[PDB]
Image 1 (cartoon, one colour):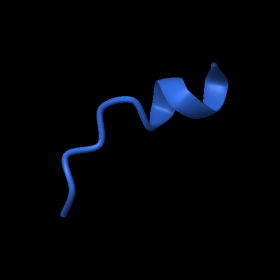
Image 2: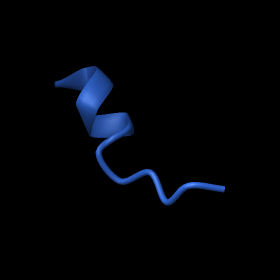
Image 3: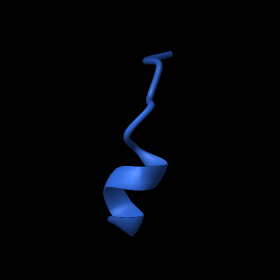
Length: 13
């Protein structure tokens, strides 16, 4: 799997 960091923040941003 990719380590998604700005995935939850990037959508809500």
